Image 1 (cartoon, rainbow over the protein chains, first blue to last red):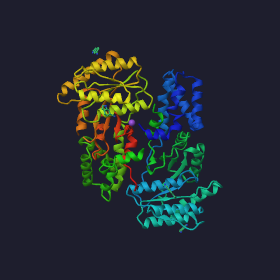
Image 2 (tube, each protein chain N blue to C red):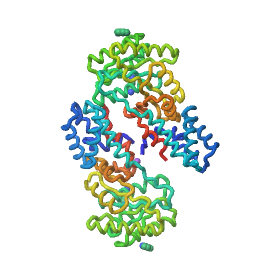
Image 3 (spheres, rainbow over the protein chains, first blue to last red):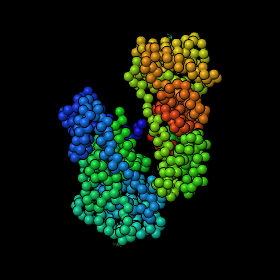
Length: 301
Length: 301
Ligand SMILES: N#Cc1ccc2cc[nH]c2c1
Ligand SMILES: N#Cc1ccc2cc[nH]c2c1
Ligand SMILES: N#Cc1ccc2cc[nH]c2c1
Ligand SMILES: N#Cc1ccc2cc[nH]c2c1
Ligand code: NA
């Protein structure tokens, strides 16, 4: 089962889920064993504190049943890691708002703009009318590409001149979305790396200006991060969460990275729903995150 | 690849998968719509019981999600139909036995003998040695076709005179396969005229097999023809008569009634090992439920 997800997770599977099978084969449960396991979890980008949590519950659970063969750790690990992901299994529901405003935050070059396009096309396939706000206002090439993408797919894109105030663009977009009975408004934002404090105050300004038109907006604050960037994904999540308060995460580029295990760190450290995972190039490969599917593909033996 | 798979399903896609799109376009979610959808599933050979389950789950999930637009039923239906096939998505693994014995059951004229040849060539291509047993012993023309095929393809075929005891032929083939360290033995009657006979003959075959290897047959594989509820009915008969462990469904291409795969999956819960979607050896595809669903529900809008 799950042949496509298993292929996407091939490099992750070398260290997590099925990768544990060779690590445990014919070993006994002792400190040597748990030390090897901790090393492997850290190599897989699971994170220092998440790994310590797993080893602790795993060691206590082994002791209680007086488990002796390391092979018996497998089911316990699958349960422990499964519960980490279950806590952030919650599909995004955009129904019933006029418009449902998604604020897309995150650094440039990690699939934020790709994710906007795929979400837009999915929502329109669902029968919703979508509009985009080109809030990354100082990147003239990014804004023009977004506008060209909108013209190609008959989706309105609200934009202003290079250097325009992003909070102004997004205000004008909410106003236009409301006038045009738009169901989902997806607002891009700047993702420059220099000067982190400036970007964060810019996002807080956007949120305050939105609330001049709708106090429930933004209805979703969605971070996009790229699994191939390993722990940098965690550090980005922390920065954006502390600044504007995330309500959802999209984790892209799971296919072809050995660092997919960063999902556990993201899930455990923040408890924010992971709404979507990106497991390939298709629109349909931005998949709603389903924890038990992910675990099954990972641990399938 | 995936593009050939989509093309091979175009006729079934008229009414299932992407065939649902025109049905939902601009409609409200009400009983008229669910009635039309139920009728469309039944026409596609999904089956009364399986259709009732799909419609019930879809209706409940639409309510809970508070859906407004019929277009949004598409993703829920893709998930419901995908879950039916996920539950029978276990691949056949023929490795590690001397020989791995596949007992091929099914009626005559549904691609059973074609499937035997394609599997034999696929296994050979993977580096495994293969033997066939001509267990359809009262049909002289069929035995000779199988012998001719084995001659043409340099694969040994164990056979006896017309009217030989099937279980004895298969007994002799397992003996020979074991002596020659053959990796895979594929054993071929499929007469439904007196079904009480055919079924008792299968139980005799299995009993005799177990004299030489208590694990044999390692797989009991039914073959049925997707272009034929006859295929649903043959699976019921063989399922109750013998313990099926796998199912091959042939001729999915060029037929517009692709729902039998869903009815078979849901009613019996037996793994679907292979689907035949064309004339080439490789068009007998190891079944991947996720690939199949994606091809069936592929949409470009
Ligand atoms: N998916 C997606 C996508 C593809 C191209 C562009 C260009 C600007 N935004 C885009 C989004
Ligand atoms: N265009 C624009 C616009 C309109 C109102 C406010 C309020 C704060 N920024 C704004 C920008
Ligand atoms: N693939 C295949 C195939 C087609 C015809 C016969 C007849 C006896 N074995 C057969 C195998
Ligand atoms: N050829 C043949 C054969 C040999 C032994 C037994 C035992 C039961 N059936 C058998 C058939
Ligand atoms: Na499968």
